Image (cartoon, rainbow, N blue to C red; front, side, top):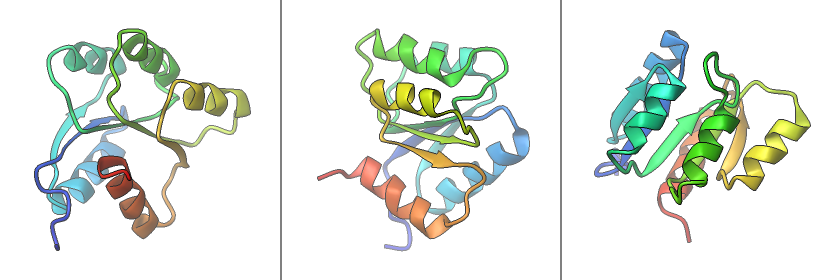
Length: 127
């Protein structure tokens, strides 16, 4: 109850180490086991070998943007649930992420961490 995410595995793709560490701290304290990847190309390779319950990522990324990563795995029949957290203002990029089937696109940096909690739970346990 204090650990609602026990048994769920969350992949976090984030190039900024501080935001990587913060997300790790927050999901781990809720009981999830975390896998963190600093690089989107690394994450693409990783997903070939495992099946996380949720993947968190950004549209904006240095090597390969998130829309590229999303399309590579979706074109490949991979229906891993994805939650995007992004500071992007670009309406067409948000729309493209939604067309690729992400659960939501949330603003970065997070303002309502209790909302993020309810939204992550719903990604992992939808109706």
